[PDB]
Amino acid sequence: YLMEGSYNKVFLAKGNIPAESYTFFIDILLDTIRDEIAGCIEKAYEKILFTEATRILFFNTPKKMTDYAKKRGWVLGPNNYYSFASQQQKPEDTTIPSTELAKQVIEYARQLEMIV
Amino acid sequence: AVQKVVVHPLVLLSVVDHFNRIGKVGNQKRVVGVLLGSWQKKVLDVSNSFAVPFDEDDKDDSVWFLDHDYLENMYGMFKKVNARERIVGWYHTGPKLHKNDIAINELMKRYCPNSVLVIIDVKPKDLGLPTEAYISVEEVHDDGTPTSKTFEHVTSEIGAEEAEEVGVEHLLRDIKDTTVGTLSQRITNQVHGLKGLNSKLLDIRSYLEKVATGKLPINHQIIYQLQDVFNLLPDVSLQEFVKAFYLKTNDQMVVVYLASLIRSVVALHNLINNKIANRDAEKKEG
Amino acid sequence: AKAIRDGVIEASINHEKGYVQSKEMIDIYSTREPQLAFHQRISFCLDI
Amino acid sequence: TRPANHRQLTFEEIAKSAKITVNEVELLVMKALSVGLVKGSIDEVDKRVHMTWVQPRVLDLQQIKGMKDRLEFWCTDVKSMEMLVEHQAHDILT
Image (cartoon, rainbow over all chains, first blue to last red; front, side, top):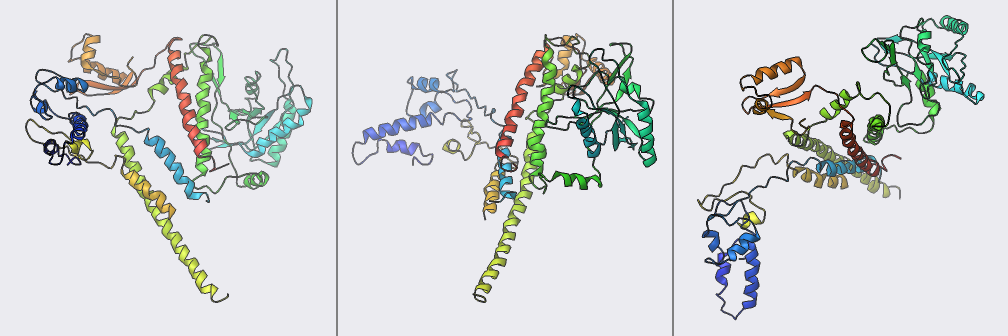
């Protein structure tokens, strides 16, 4: 269930143990998905109020949303999570194929006429 | 008016052998001679030449002499042996543009209208062609002198001839990077080409030496073209120019992928043509 | 959410409304994948 | 003044730097193109003009410092890219 996007079922398995305690393992299991929800806040979402993504983890209203909201963006505003969905800078690169392809063209010319 | 020049290796060596035959003076002597030949279809031609007797003293270097009797008689011999051959101009040995080569051309302009000169090289080293020709233009312009005249270099190259290529290719016998395939352009203009851009890059760097220290005339007619270089500097990588570049490249490796796909099958057919020469020969002969 | 995390699908979700929008991504041609599909097989067909 | 980056000005900027109204700047720039002091194109709907070629002017000993510097690192691009040519194209011809 950790393989796919099954989150809620994993947090249902957090507490539904028939075998033994498993407490130290579901506390690592807690942190390693805390930074995973704290990762998947970073999409091209819209404005989310201070209830929805406030309750996607396991909290009502502590300052843990101040810990995440000052940790990453989606800044604390008037019931607002700010979307800096930019993804703008990296394209329009002619020079990198004009270096790599400039290597690979001559590398095509090496095993083309010269005897090996 | 004049498109370009055509220079033969026979006259090209036929100046340097004169530099050998007056190289016994040791001190200083320039090979100045009369350049003979034609020009047809506004294409300048250079076939034959000789050299005129010339001396020059360092003090008061505004004095030249050409023996015009020697100019008349040997050229009359040359017309008599060859009525097709005629005058085309003159030449000097041209290390570094000696000063009498502003009025040598005015001295013998009465023979050829475009009495063109040719600067040659006696110590051959460059990354290009050490063959030069100017053209005479005079100017009554606003600035400069009222009587002003400055030579302008028409482009220069070595024209060939089907007769002379037998002797040229005979006299090479040294190295010749023929079998022009995927590699000859790579070295004649891609290794050598960017280094051809090196010298033209470095030449405006050589003009650049006058920032506050060099010669006294500043720009006037140098900087409109320099401004036009940075102005006409090509397009940056934002447009579909990028996407059309990817498009046609991505079209080109289709063709390369096709022929590359054919070649291995060709050599596979050549492999089966060898296994038939293996198995049906080893049992027969032994 | 993890389908945007792991790569697969790229575009946005309107979690407030409900709809998941997806852009029309055409002209993968200029994008430098089929040159790699070439280059995997150029050198390999030269190998055979 | 504008670099080779954009050099794309607007009719509001002509109305600012020349204090002349919106309905006359096109009659100005058609005359500039007819004289041929400038060479560029005119958009009307986005109110911008793609100026390409300008009449070349004169300059003092300060602009040759900038043209000097823009020449300077343009040398090492030819050095750097030709360096790959002689290195990778080494064995192709001796």
